[PDB]
Amino acid sequence: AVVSTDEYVARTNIYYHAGTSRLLAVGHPYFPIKKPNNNKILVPKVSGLQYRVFRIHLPDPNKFGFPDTSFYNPDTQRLVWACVGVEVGRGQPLGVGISGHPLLNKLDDTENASAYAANAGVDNRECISMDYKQTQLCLIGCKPPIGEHWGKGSPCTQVAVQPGDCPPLELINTVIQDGDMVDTGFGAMDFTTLQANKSEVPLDICTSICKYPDYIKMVSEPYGDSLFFYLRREQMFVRHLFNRAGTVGENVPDDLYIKGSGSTANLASSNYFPTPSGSMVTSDAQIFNKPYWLQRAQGHNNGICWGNQLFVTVVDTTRSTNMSLCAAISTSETTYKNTNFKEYLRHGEEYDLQFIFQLCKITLTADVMTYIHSMNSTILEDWNEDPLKKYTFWEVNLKEKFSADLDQFPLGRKFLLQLGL
Amino acid sequence: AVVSTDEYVARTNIYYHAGTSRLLAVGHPYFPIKKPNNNKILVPKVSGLQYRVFRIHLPDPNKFGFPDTSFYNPDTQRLVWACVGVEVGRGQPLGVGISGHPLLNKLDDTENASAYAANAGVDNRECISMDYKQTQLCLIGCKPPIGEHWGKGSPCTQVAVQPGDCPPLELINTVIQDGDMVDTGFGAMDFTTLQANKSEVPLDICTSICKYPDYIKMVSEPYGDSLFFYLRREQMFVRHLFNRAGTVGENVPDDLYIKGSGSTANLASSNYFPTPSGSMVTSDAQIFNKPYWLQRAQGHNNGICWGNQLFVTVVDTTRSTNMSLCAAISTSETTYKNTNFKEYLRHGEEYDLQFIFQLCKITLTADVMTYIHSMNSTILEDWNEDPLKKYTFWEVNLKEKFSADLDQFPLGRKFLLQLGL
Amino acid sequence: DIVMTQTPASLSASVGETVTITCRASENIYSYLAWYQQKQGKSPQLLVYNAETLAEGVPSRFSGSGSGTQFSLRINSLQPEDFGSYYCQHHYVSPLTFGAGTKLELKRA
Amino acid sequence: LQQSGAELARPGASVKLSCKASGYTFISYWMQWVKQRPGQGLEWIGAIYPGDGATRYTQKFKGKATLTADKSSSTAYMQLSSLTSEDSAVYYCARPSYYDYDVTWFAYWGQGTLVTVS
């Protein structure tokens, strides 16, 4: 049986503040710029539509050097940091981005038509853009976040897959890494392995995987380390209604309609797809630049940062403004020439993480050691190499950022005022 | 360590009201009208999209002549004014402006296309306008406000910048001056130094810098003098989705799509940009013509106006209506002729600042003098030339506007009623 | 690779005469066809691009036509400076390939 | 697009051909390379975008031709190796005007370099 951390984790009266200086990210909104002949990344892909997963490193409270050490017995017990307050600061002005594809698979406009559309020739793709669905979310836990997305399942050993056959789906749980893409209106799926077309969605998710937090699984989690607090805000509506060029993969059963003739003799593509649109963005609806007091967790782990680690996942598309900057090739001619200017795109993201941590102690009794051992053996082993080296996240080192004077910081003042004493 | 002003600043029981008569500003919405041969400004640029930074001058409470002076010892202590109430009155009817450019770099409409767009020739710019993003904000502090915007960073001494090469970005902190422009939907950047094109955005921000308050930095500020109170309200949505003419600065990696042919042989510009739109403006959402009671500040400076100064920054695009007024060249012919009429544009702004100040006293002990000296040595020096002469703001002189009869003023009545005694 | 079949290989004509040179693609190239003229001992010069659009300095007596796999270049009322070789080339995707060439020569007794 | 008049090469060796651009914003365009032998027609070798090094090669010339560029001198280069008599030909560099998908023309050609393997 699992139990609340309140059971075996003792709360001291010491509180520390810690914060990143001001994280900054600048890159190209749709894809990374690199050397053609090469593969090193010259400019990274930085979009408001990516997940930001911060791997927060905390100084080991056991190795830490406190002015007073009488508050606990280093023989019978151990120390752990507990997250009690978080403030995810965001810094650019609010705004909406936009993504498209020069060769998007869009046959005709099916929202309203005055005459039956022509006939699909070869390549009817159009240069189309759209404003993705709005998403604001923040996940916090001592384990990395877990997402879900549809991918190509493994086929059953029977009917040999005929080329072009529809691929099998399978919900796939994955670890959400920093840089991953958020569902943008086309759901959470692996477009690379499910769309040979390479033109079904805009470039920025075109050969990526849009993942969605698997809230259900994470909350079901017995110990609840992956996430002990979260905030989600997503909205979307249909801007346009289109058709998909290509060839019928599955035909429309003729019991569903009466055969046409002449122009209506041949059925038009009924493989419709809508264009998303996350409406207006607003201050009043902001989730960030507000402090979150993690006092009572719904999970059994009440904000204990086992391993002196802490994960802060974020997605904010309310500041997705992309800015185009173009340089002139020549500063002479006083007559505009499209050839004289090189057009580019860049997007900037600005963060500022702040936390309030509460020191905690654990008397290492038999029972306690049995429990913690079962829960996560590494805890004890580390007490008196990186297990997620495979994954990549924005590494954040706070070992030199703890300060006992909450007074001197904005989140700290807020905390004192809020907790009174 | 920094400490709240409540520590060393004593509060008296004297309160004064002060207010500007009614500030008025009339000018051209997009650019200043001046003599071609000359450089003297004939008509200034006045837009609802500019920041209004008021430099409020207060009478030195030490030089001031109070009816009674027994309330303090002019030998051991000094006096300072503390801002306790502010009312930013606005006076025109609510309405939305509109800005454009006769030669905006807009290739084609990428929101929905029925056939692949033609081919960029020479200068495909269009005469286009848009309704900027809505913004309402008010910053108050005893130091001028600080903003952030992206500019052209300094290049690394290596690879010689090939002409047309994309310029490097750099977040630049600046002092927000009166007349500066607010992000309008294209983010906060220096369009002059980042867009040689001179046609990426409407005329009014076209060769300016759109700055965004750097709230994060200002609140982190140790003493918190730059801003001890603020109200922000911004909203925006995508009205249109366009393409940028010009030449590929960075090519689309071919691993992101399947080569076309014929018409789709050549990739259309995937340098998309959206047209902003601050939706409807409403009374219910007004931030002004409401009193702000600055009682508990989140910073350590609790509304103390060191230097007998006070800064009030404002941005209100909810009254951005521009009015076109045209004069006839001849009052004869009863037949309309475009040419008989000269069309112009003008925009008016109406303000009315009101404040409630509380007299305060500081006993100049050793510790206090050491602290205040470290904080801002000029404080003491001035006690028993302009350090920001470089910057420009709407100068407001209130030295002759203080009145002890709050009773006689609207903000005054409100204050009394609010504070009871 | 994509093959451009250009005919005739050789064509004789008089000044004032209208002639047509054709180019057929092995597979669909849409409208992305170009045409070049190459005079004796000189480098090629582009006359037509995007199947039918006149290039810089090309007289209006020249006209390109076609879209898909069949194209043609027509020269109305031939002038003395029009004799020489002509080549078609698609510019849809890489690899770029050329037609075999047509040698347009002047008829005499 | 200035090209040197001729190159004399020994069988089996390599040759480096230059193309000097002038009169336009070099970094805004690709560079085309085309082969011409007296008996046959024109043959495309490949094209390069100096702005980032992107190349496209005729399958026939993959492993034979290398394309590069020197943005500081506005010069495009092509190198051929393992030269045989079949490589003796006049090689031209040319430009590709691209403004949009429907406005493009590769209309300006250099004078060509006669490469003779002997």
Image: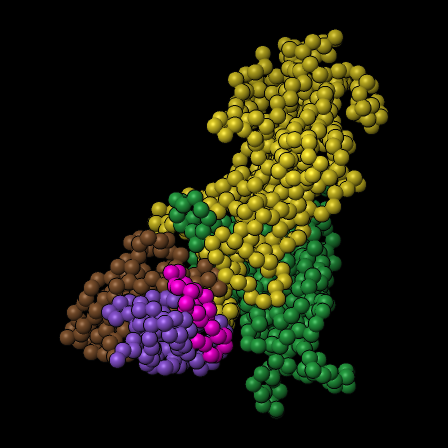
Chain colours: A green, B yellow, C purple, D brown
Tell me which segment is drawn in magenta. C49-72
Residue A63 is situated, as x and y percent measured from the top left of the image, at 53, 50
**Quadrant of residue A265 in the image?**
bottom right
Residue drawn at (59%, 60%) of the image: B110
Residue drawn at (73%, 39%) of the image: B95
Residue B133 is situated, as x and y percent measured from the top left of the image, at 66, 45
Residue B317 is situated, as x and y percent measured from the top left of the image, at 68, 39
In the displayed structure, would residue C75 be above or below residue A21? below
- Farthest residue to the front: give it: C109
**Quadrant of residue D49 in the image?**
bottom left
Residue A5 shows in the view = no
In the displayed structure, would residue B126 be above or below residue B44? below
Q: In the drawing, does residue B222 fall left or right of residue A418?
A: left
In the displayed structure, would residue A220 be above or below residue B147? below
Residue drawn at (49%, 52%) of the image: B123
Question: Nearest the camera: A168 or A373?
Answer: A168
Q: In the drawing, does residue B70 fall left or right of residue A59?
A: right
